[PDB]
Image (tube, grey):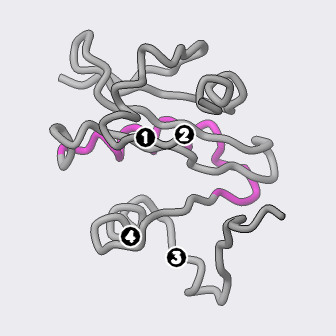
Amino acid sequence: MITIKKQEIVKLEDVLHLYQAVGWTNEMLEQALSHSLVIYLALDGDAVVGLIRLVGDGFSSVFVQDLIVLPSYQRQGIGSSLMKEALGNFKEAYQVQLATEETEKNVGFYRSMGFEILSTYDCTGMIWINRE
């Protein structure tokens, strides 16, 4: 049913429906898509139903920047598949990280993928809020 395909060029038109599906806010994104380490798509025949996008230097640091499945699919291992194929390229990267809404669903899913929350190690993510 579902195809996981590595992508070399990803144009925003072909994936904008996925970001809309979550949405939206803010594009930097057109530019971002060219400057990522890797992108995989999830395909239901010809339909684009999921995306993973990794960023970073690819050696010391890799970040799971976008992980999207259409909320209409899901719970059939699409997110897992996307994660396992993309991260397979980076199995020796020094640190691999991500930031998520801290819900039981999100956290339970990333833990099933082998990720742990930073507080378990007395660490924290921080985000730039005040730029002046």
Residue closest to the far front: 132
The Cα atoms of the two marked residues, 1 and 3, are separated by: 26 Å
Image: magenta residue range: 76-96
Q: Residues within 10 Å of mark 1 (few under 14, many from 20)?
A: few
Q: Which residue is mark 1?
A: 24
Location of residue 103 with respect to 28 vertically, above or below = below
Residue 132 covered by magenta stretch = no
Figure quadrant of the C terminus = bottom right
Dot 1 and dot 4 residues touching (CB under 8 Å) = no
82 sits to left or right of 98 = left
Reading the chain from its start, which is encountered first: label 4 or label 3? 4
Mark nearer the viewer, 2 or 4: 2
Give the secondary structure at mark 1: loop
User: Which residue sits at x=54%, y=62%?
Assistant: 99
Residue type for callout 1: Trp
Give the secondary structure at mark 2: loop
Q: Which mark is residue 90?
A: none
The chief SS type of the magenta part is helix
Task: Pick the residue in front: 111 or 31.
Answer: 31
Q: Which mark is residue 26?
A: 2
Q: Which residue is mark 4?
A: 107
Q: Which residue is mark 3?
A: 117
Give the secondary structure at mark 3: loop
Mark nearer the viewer, 1 or 3: 1
